[PDB]
Image (cartoon, rainbow over all chains, first blue to last red):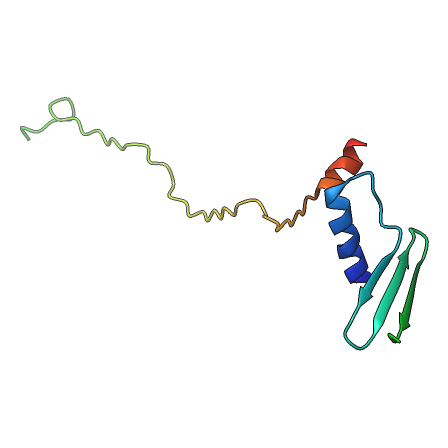
Length: 50
Length: 49
């Protein structure tokens, strides 16, 4: 998960350098993945779609 | 009797020759290393910033 977020952060970063990732949410067919990224720590929560 | 010390003079002449020598020399080019560099707009901006 962190490798995807780092790659995802760069994708957001390429379009605007000043803009920095605040929150990223990936929704799979059977599950929803939410990752909150900070320099000190990263919080990842997996919640099944209702 | 005809040959005389004054009549015939013998001189020995030689040419200086450098002594032959055997030497082995090995040359090997400077060590080369593999370098991988990835450049992104944000990374360039961060250094610039």
